[PDB]
Every structure is written in C-alpha cells, then in structure tokens.
Image (cartoon, rainbow over all chains, first blue to last red; front, side, top):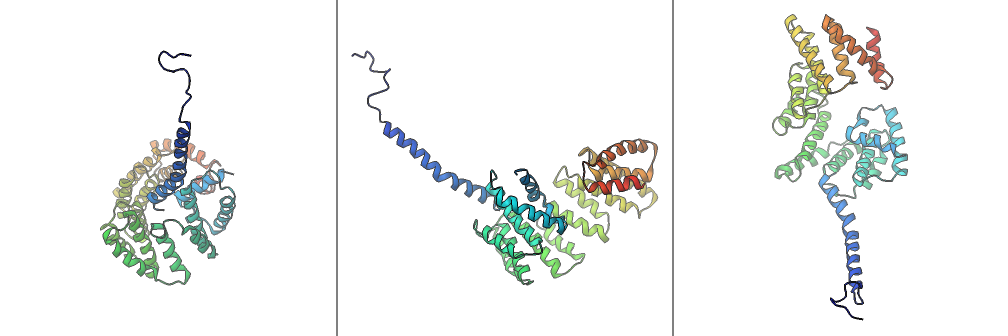
Length: 49
Length: 290
C-alpha cells in the first residue's frame, strides 16, 4: 500500500487523541472554576447591593 | 407561577410597598413568601438578593419584626456589611431594636470616613438621605429640615431628583408655592420624561393662582394648561394630566377648551373604564360629581 503525498485520506494511525481530549477537559474545568465565581463576584460587586 | 415575579420586579424598582395599606401590605408579604420559598426557578441571583432585602424591609414595615433579623442574618453573607444597603439595614435595626439614636453617631464618623470617598457618591447620597430621615425624628418636624437639606443638597448633590422632589412637599404644604415650581422644573432637568412632575408642576401653579391677582390668575392658569398638556404628550390614559386639563377647563370652559373638554372627556371616560382599579373611584368621582 503506497501513498504518493503521504496519507491525507486516513484519519491517522497515530493521533494524540488523549492530549486533545484532556485539553478539552481543561476547558471544561476552567469553566467550572470561573462561572459561579465570576458571575457572583462581578454582578454583586459592581452593583454593590 | 412565574407571573408572580413580575410584581416583585416592579416592587423592587418602584418601592410600591412604601405607600401600601398595612392590610394589603400584610397580604403582600404573605403572597410573597409562598412564591419566594416555592418558585425558586429561572431568576437571577441579583434579583434574589434584591427580593430578599425587599422582604426584610417589608417585614420591618410589617408589625412583627423579629423575622427581619432572620432575613438580615441570611442576607449578611455577601459583601459583608460595607455596601450602602447593609449600612441602611444596620442603622434601621439599631434604631428600631431599642429606639436608641446610636446608629447616627456610628454613621456620623462614617461620613467623616467618606471624606476620602471610601465609597461611591450614591452611597453617601443615600446615607445623607437616611441620616436626615433619622434627624427628622430627632427633630420631630420643622421647615428647617429643608434648610438642613440645603447644606446637604445645594452643597453636595443637586443631581438626586428625589431631594428636590421631597423639598417640594415641604415648600408646598405651608411654604411659598412658587419655589416648588422652580424645584419641579429642576426635576425635569434631571430626567426628561417624568410625567408626574408634570402634573404636580401644574397643580402647584394652580394653587398659587388661587391666591394671586386676576392677570396672574389667567397667566398661571394658561401656563398650567400648557404644563398639563405637556403631561398628555407623555401618556394617553394618564389620569392626572387629563384630569387637570379638564379641571382648569371646568374652571374656564371657553369655546376651544370646550372641544378639549369633549376630547378629554372621551379620554377620561376611557381612563375611568374599569381597566384601571381604585384610581377609577377618584376619576369617576370628579367625572360624575361635576
């Protein structure tokens, strides 16, 4: 089996899918960190209720 | 039922509770608590705590007040006590809990600590308002309360329309009825579209005209017409602008105003239609009386 250009059709045999998935999870955890924090902090601090 | 929160949204922004009968206020607090405890869905935290303090202030308005301590303790969690509201809650608590004057002096140095502007301008604007509200209990009533307002109003913050509006009342009750016209004009300066300062600014002219000369009577009545007509452009069913137009037209009754009486009568009967509640009783009373 021969590839003229190197394989462009095959997805890969050798992705670092684990790195991609973990980076996505890093996004989700940082959401979990900031959203209650920033929503409470800024809305209630700038309104000075 | 989420329709409930609509009134609550009004009641925070409008302070509708302030002029409510303790019978309907007691109903209001009972009707509130069921939705406050039950319908906890889909409403913001900021609305939550605005509703929570508005529960506190209803409860202090209520005749039982121990629950006020409950609500305050639960609401003391956030931003400590330094915001304008917790200064209000602690002052009214310290003033009501024992009928001791103490909070004022504990608030007095606070304004002397506001010499650095440690808090925003609206904060000690409201502190000036509520410390004067304390002081008019210290000095139970007088016209010099307004003179106190001047050292608080014309020195520090013309911008609060509430201050000029309140000053109008003390001028209007027994003071000269002309400086209320100036102050209500200043209210118009602050906000473009206050349509109840429009009705009042005409009423104070009318009451001034009742004690004036004939040429000033006609002059002030004509200005009152043009101010009440200025009311009308901001609203269709506004009961007080249309009514005050019709009132001075009842007084004068001259041909072109007789047409405006017919038009105002159609609009005032539309107002006195039952779309409006209780206000209709005052509207119909003047309509059918004369």
